[PDB]
Length: 250
Length: 250
Image 1 (cartoon, rainbow over the protein chains, first blue to last red):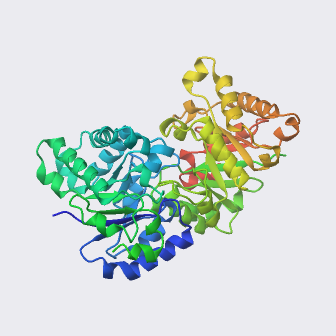
Image 2 (cartoon, rainbow over the protein chains, first blue to last red; image 1 turned 90 degrees about the vertical axis):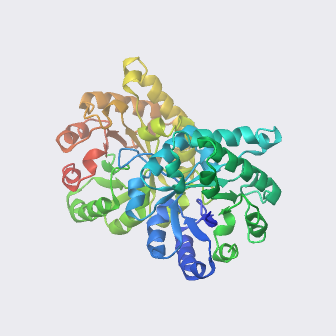
Image 3 (cartoon, rainbow over the protein chains, first blue to last red; image 1 turned 180 degrees about the vertical axis):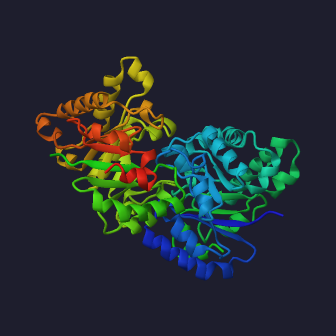
């Protein structure tokens, strides 16, 4: 058993008025069409309280786009999991490409976040992915191996029921250049093996973990991705950010 | 006279329940006693929409603890000034010591944020200060000059009406070791001198810029700091986070 998950990442792309409309539209339309799939949305932190109240009691899960690895404390500009848990947000994204690249987040910083969140009973959506240059220099595996082994260092297998992974090759993020199903399937099968290999032969762990694909996922390409054996859903940026393309993914 | 500002930084120290209680108490209490002084508060991002609503139409200014240098766009986990303007937040802190040390913010990154915010008609509260080690080693002036010069690189005179500085020596942040009034004055005097030297005519604008002191400010020490010629207010951490100590600053 693996969950199929369609997650929307609103990034920093929406106004509050857009986010609020989107949430109301989502509550109205998605539960009835989601079927066996889990639906999830990651609004900007500034809108999370609002959107969390709108979606409360619905089957649509709300997650945060980032946090810091501390309970309430003196970290100017940061969001605490203590603050998220208070408003009922229990899923946090870690290691998104934009944070790696533009906010300089390393695999070690990711690991600190993941351990804190898993220890404190959060669910974590951890992003991994290579750049165009890494892919073109035959480094794809080295990068992804590193992201997984260093990101997930020191985490016992019992916490893996609360971990979700996303493969988002940087060359596909916002460029309109979606990985083909074979390309994505190849990478997902490698990732799944790495997860097994963390605990040595942990097939039950690796077969139970959802591994989502992201990077230019749209209504007209999602289905062929979801058909692949090791693709368990979509992490969706631009196309999650209007109700009509978001509903069109289900 | 330059304006006196008393600004509270709630960092990541408060629950929503606490932020709400504090915002209400502040609304009830501060406007009657602030008099000539500008009052300002910086809630955590997750709480800004709520606190902003609570304080809307009061004389208490709401500011954000950090943002990114872009309008709406694909930067997962970040907050846009577009999103802040929308809920009425028009003052943003840049370069707080916790972000420089724990989130790796450089002078140049700060300069990017300051330029973007000032260009977009925000008010910027730019934080400078040296560590204990830098102070002890003879680098106080080198560090502060650097932070000022690199931070304000390429900013036009036209925008200085919307710049506020805060000196927060890192050895005074949360340590209970406040700078003496002389120690603070001497560095404020230096900071103002640095501003005056940024370009021909600068001295004509440097007397207008508010320079606040921060680091272990409390009711029993604020008055003596404010008496100093180049100290134009306070940026207050811990003592701002409860109504009775915040009000005792006024």
